[PDB]
Image (cartoon, grey):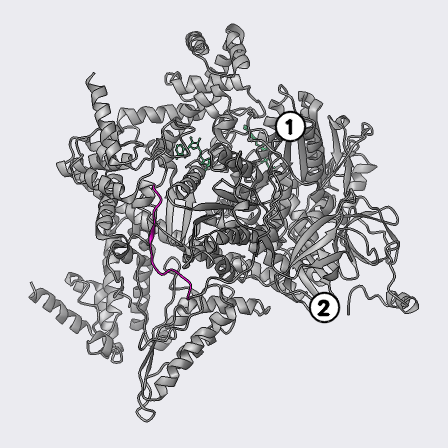
Amino acid sequence: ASELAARMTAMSNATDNANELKKTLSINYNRARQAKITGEILEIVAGANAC
Amino acid sequence: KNLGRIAQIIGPVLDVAFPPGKMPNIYNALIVKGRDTAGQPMNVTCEVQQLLGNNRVRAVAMSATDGLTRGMEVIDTGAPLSVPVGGATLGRIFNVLGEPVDNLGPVDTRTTSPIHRSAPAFTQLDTKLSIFETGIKVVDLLAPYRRGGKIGLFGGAGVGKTVLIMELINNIAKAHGGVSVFGGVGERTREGNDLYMEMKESGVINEQNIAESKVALVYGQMNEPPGARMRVGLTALTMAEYFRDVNEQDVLLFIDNIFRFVQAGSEVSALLGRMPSAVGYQPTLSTEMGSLQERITSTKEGSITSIQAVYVPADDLTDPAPATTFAHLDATTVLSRGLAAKGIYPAVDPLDSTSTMLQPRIVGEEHYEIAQRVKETLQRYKELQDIIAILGLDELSEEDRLTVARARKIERFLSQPFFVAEVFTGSPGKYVGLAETIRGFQLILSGELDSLPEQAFYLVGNIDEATAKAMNLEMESKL
Amino acid sequence: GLTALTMAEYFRDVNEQDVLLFIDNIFRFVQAGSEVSALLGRMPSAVGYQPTLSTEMGSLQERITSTKEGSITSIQAVYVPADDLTDPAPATTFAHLDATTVLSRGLAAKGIYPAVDPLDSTSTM
Amino acid sequence: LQPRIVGEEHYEIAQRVKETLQRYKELQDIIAILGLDELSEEDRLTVARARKIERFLSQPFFVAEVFTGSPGKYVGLAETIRGFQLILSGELDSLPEQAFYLVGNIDEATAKAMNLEMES
Amino acid sequence: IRADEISKIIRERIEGYNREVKVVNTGTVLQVGDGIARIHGLDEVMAGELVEFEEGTIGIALNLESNNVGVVLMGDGLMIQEGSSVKATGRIAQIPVSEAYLGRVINALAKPIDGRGEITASESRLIESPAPGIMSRRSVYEPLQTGLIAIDAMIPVGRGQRELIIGDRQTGKTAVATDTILNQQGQNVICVYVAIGQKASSVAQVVTNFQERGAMEYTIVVAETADSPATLQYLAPYTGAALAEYFMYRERHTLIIYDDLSKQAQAYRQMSLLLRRPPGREAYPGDVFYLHSRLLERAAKLSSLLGEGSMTALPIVETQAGDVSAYIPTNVISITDGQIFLSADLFNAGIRPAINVGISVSRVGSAAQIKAMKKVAGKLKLELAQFAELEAFAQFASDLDKATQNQLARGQRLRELLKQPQSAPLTVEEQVMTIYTGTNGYLDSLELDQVRKYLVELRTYVKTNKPEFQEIISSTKTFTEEAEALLKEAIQEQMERFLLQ
Amino acid sequence: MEYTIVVAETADSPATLQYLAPYTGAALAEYFMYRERHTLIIYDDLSKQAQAYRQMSLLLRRPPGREAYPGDVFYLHSRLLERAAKLSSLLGEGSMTALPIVETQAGDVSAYIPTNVISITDGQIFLSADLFNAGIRPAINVGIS
Ligand SMILES: Nc1ncnc2c1ncn2[C@@H]1O[C@H](COP(=O)(O)OP(=O)(O)OP(=O)(O)O)[C@@H](O)[C@H]1O
Ligand SMILES: Nc1ncnc2c1ncn2[C@@H]1O[C@H](COP(=O)(O)OP(=O)(O)O)[C@@H](O)[C@H]1O
């Protein structure tokens, strides 16, 4: 029973650490995707400005 | 009148050649006398977007351009787009041009108003932040609206978003002296027809007595060019704005939905060839959103409350369109598929939905504390959702057993029998003021009605009808 | 590419025999089109390829086909820039290629050769 | 940072600090989700040493004395190399982490440790 | 250094400047290359009007500029010379359309490429007509049986609904499309299949397949191969829509397959960049949403007076690396009603058709379902929701309570239910059979693999030995207690004989 | 309001006016600052001014960068801010305190305009969405402020 309570505490902490990790990673991903799309559009319009 | 010829056309962007003296202003609507394949005159409309000089403007079409010819006659109307307004438009479908498409009859109203206008002055606003009372228990207690403020609508299909809209119209019509308007910015035509028929059946549009209806529907479909789908919102706005500036009626302005207006403006700027901003929106995203989100206020005369749907693309709350929209929004009500699938209608989640209006110094300390205790009980229920199943509901402590019991009572009392969903269900519609609401939750949560069955609070109006139904259920259970 | 294709097309047309047409590398054809596009006067499309990309790949692939007379079997290799199958030219060749095999840097780096990524590789046969 | 310039002792201790900090940087992804409990004996050893190391790298400055309140310490190479030699040898393994935080010399670190054991 | 100023036109104007006279009778070719041609004159030509180059090369006057008409070439020009005289035509992109198109293969000019013979037609329909209006439609009523248990239960498609098929490379989009088309032999619909930028060999495979199946008796297969011009690849789906709406307006039901719209959008962006139009995302023009909206919304369920005709658009878009929030995916997802989302990780895992049941949606919904289908589909959807929640508990099937163990068991068998062989479409009654056998709980006994063989044997045994069931459902379209008892009887009979094997 | 002057340009005002308004506030403040009077100016926000400047810069076909912000987007803020000083004792000691406001999406301090403003101002008072939504108002995060 002590070992299973220990594993339950380990999971109750590790799943929430994985929660905060997925949240901060999704935020970094949103910023990165926004920057990528902006860079691609700006490099497209740079060629149009060249012509 | 002022006559000019078409210089060049590139899709819905036309150029018009006026003589040196006469030349329209910015945003001046332009009728273009044009033909059809049957030879029939078809008047295609525009709006001057740029005075590009050399006595030649660059106007953006509001209709189909195929068939228009270089050198056709364009007449300068000399003023921004003037739509038909007033009580004539009630129960009538419209376009971006204010020209109706229900084939009922012509709008014989003489009153027009320009689609373009400045926001109400700073010496005009009604500074009192008041909670716009709706009659729905969930959105009254947990997501209280403000009058003259903007309210975002977050609901994926099947949660009763349209039934919620029709109920909101019905309540603003019956309780108050209000009138609603619906602006379908980019509305797929099949669902536009669906909504029109559901309003015909739900009595929101009295098909037998037009102008006794409660709504003036403005449908600008996805079929229409990108120039039209943007100005649809301004059309609906000015048609609503008449209803409160002159008649001082509490108007509801539904915009479904804001993101598609934002991307329609993005398409217009793209066609116009102005350099893009960040991830792909138009450079004037903030100013364009302002031009539509600052006519929605509560002036000294009336109040426009904007209940607009919002859509988040790529799940971003930080994409420019959601970010700018949220910068304007005042309260968000979020509808969840969980409550729809279960049967607690409306399907509003009292935790995902929040308001900035639920401050104590706005709503009263009693309302605030009851809302806080309700939120705490429902949150503790979500936290115990997994615990109770494994532990058994009896092995819980007395405090947590009380919590789950009262949480079930509260979650079931959040259900309401709708005025417009009675045609489907069979339960009569009900209206619940905040007095009934706060006292009902005080009784349920204060441990006083903790001796009633779960079902006695389900789809009930107020706590008095809850007690009545409880006595019925107990007599029905004895024998 | 079009030179070798016209030679093989003669071989299949009049000498009416099966042909093997190995191409390597086929991405460099679209590469050259992209290099020459902007200087010719065309506006740059997405990430840098020519606007005439789909029809360029058409003018190669649809010319390369098996007929009643002869059958051109063509085992051609598509370079993928930075292993991104989202890149337009690898994305475009996929529509014309019947049997496709995708090499994965994981399988190549681990030491499993040939490095054909099996679950991503699909055939129509 | 080449021995021909800086001396073999300086170079070697720099390589060992870089090694241990690299290993902790690797184990960061694991420990974020799991915790230090799930690591091996040598892994947990390296992680504890890396904590002590990355805190001993810290030094209070004379110009930051207005924000920290603590008098900045000046500590050159003769004490830098020696202190790091000791930390990576593990003689000071009995000391906590906060003894190496915001000190100039390893002696000041040890004195702060003696204070952290005076405050029972 | 200006276009339209060729130092020969200035000569002609210096000769004839006296006053600016109409010159629409004539038109000359100034600049020509990569599929477009800038044209002088033609001052009264419309937008979209066919302009006919000398030597026979049709073009379309897309963007009329200041003094030059930018024209897309409806072929490979490469022979029109500078200064050659173009004549206008007056027509705006029409196709002749008749019932004799049923059963043939055509290019985007509605001109046959099967080599059989010419298609006699009388009435012409414009290619870019306007859609049915806000007051010329009817709310979706009638179920279009696609033949897939999963779709016909969980993502119900209707007649007049624009249900999008979206996926990655090789997830089975064309597979589900042909599956539906081959299901609709029985009921009376016209199928349309518009291929944009695909291999002539792939069009040959699908056409030969419909031939050996018999579904060529009601289909028109528009084909536009990759080498074809961007304008023809762009104009293909609109020719498909014109053909389809001709049959629609004559009270008949249609189904059209845009396979795909991604290549149509790519041809459009190619042309728009080629005749110098401002780019947007991925160098698409602003008008790609306008394009897709017009084309899609041309297809809907007409009202009662106009004949109750309808036209289901079943478009396809292919998504790259699961970027379903890209430009053309978000466009088509916004315009369409439903989305049938296909996933390659299920496709590899064996679950074919590889639809993604948690992502897929249809805002028509159970309205377009048979009553028997909805009676079984409610229970089916609840069971699948439950197993979808319990998916992260299958490894722990050794120490879960037996109730969630049995929910895992039921969802495990239900996954075995929904798989189907390639292009083998089922009828609504057989699908009701399958979903009933599943949802009631009659497959817990048989192990995880036999379920498919058991169910096919079940359907055949019912078909042979209780022919009242299919008749009951064909007559009433309602799952009635009599057919329920009959199906229970047939099920246990087949189970016994199969177990004695 | 006996002390206060409110220079207001709301959302649906020309981006040029939203770009001008902080400088009107700055001139007003400086007038009193130079004649031996202390001032306190509250810009709200600088990121909205940065967006207005981006709009009126991309409307001029100006080469942008770093999330489409123009080249002079640091020059904008530094010009506006660096005229806030505690004056010398010769010029009358009148000082203009400036407390600009900046909004962050998803707490993106590492964004272009937040890091630019941070590299100008003499500190930061970072408010926290989780702290403010947990009831600890005001939500000053003294860990990083
Ligand atoms: N439901 C299914 N059951 C078994 N096999 C299938 C199924 N669907 C597709 N397949 C197999 O997958 C292969 C790819 O199918 P299909 O060509 O329809 O995918 P696609 O999406 O059209 O590919 P692309 O996107 O490249 O056009 C086919 O060869 C077919 O044999
Ligand atoms: N308030 C409600 N009361 C009862 N039923 C409702 C309610 N809202 C939605 N429904 C159910 O949902 C359906 C309508 O949902 P609808 O508003 O059309 O959502 P959507 O348009 O997103 O599909 C009806 O069939 C009804 O049975």
Q: Which mark is residue C25?
A: none
Is residue E85 or residue F46 the one in the foreground? F46
- Vertical order, C116 against D28 (above or below): above
* Kind of residue indicated by mark 1: Leu
Q: Is residue B204 visible?
A: yes
Mark toward the viewer: 1 or 2: 1
Question: Which chain does tag 1 point to?
Answer: E
Where the N terminus of chain F falls, by quadrant? bottom left
* Kind of residue indicated by mark 2: Asn
Residue identified by numbered label 2 = B55
Is residue F102 or residue F109 the one in the foreground? F102
Where the C terminus of chain F falls, by quadrant? bottom left
Query: What range is drawn magenta here?
Result: B123-135
Question: Which chain does tag 2 point to?
Answer: B
Judged left or right of residue B265, residue E213 is: right
Tell whether position B126 is magenta.
yes
Please tell me which residue is depicted at 67% across the width and 31% down the height of the picture.
Answer: E192
Q: Are marks 1 and 2 in contact (CB under 8 Å)?
A: no
Position of residue C102 measured from the top left corner of the image (x, y, whole percent): 56, 43
Q: Secondary structure at mark 1?
A: loop
- Quadrant where ligand 2 appears: top left
Judged left or right of residue E221, residue B303 is: left
Tell whether position F77 is magenta.
no
